[PDB]
Image (tube, rainbow, N blue to C red; front, side, top):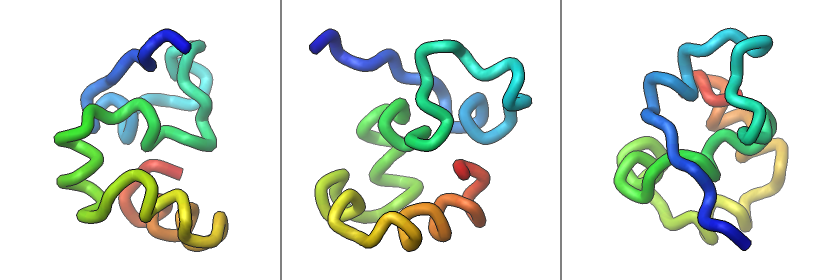
Length: 67
């Protein structure tokens, strides 16, 4: 599929739900971070993060303003 559009970390964290770009799945904001931002925010690979239980992915994101 087409490579996902990336958005700055500050935009994904600080945008009202109603104003979120239509192409962003609000439950998977991490997928729209650049690889650099994902690494800075989570400190692990995308696949390692995806292997954590869903509730743990969400809980980590909540504190980080991404869920």
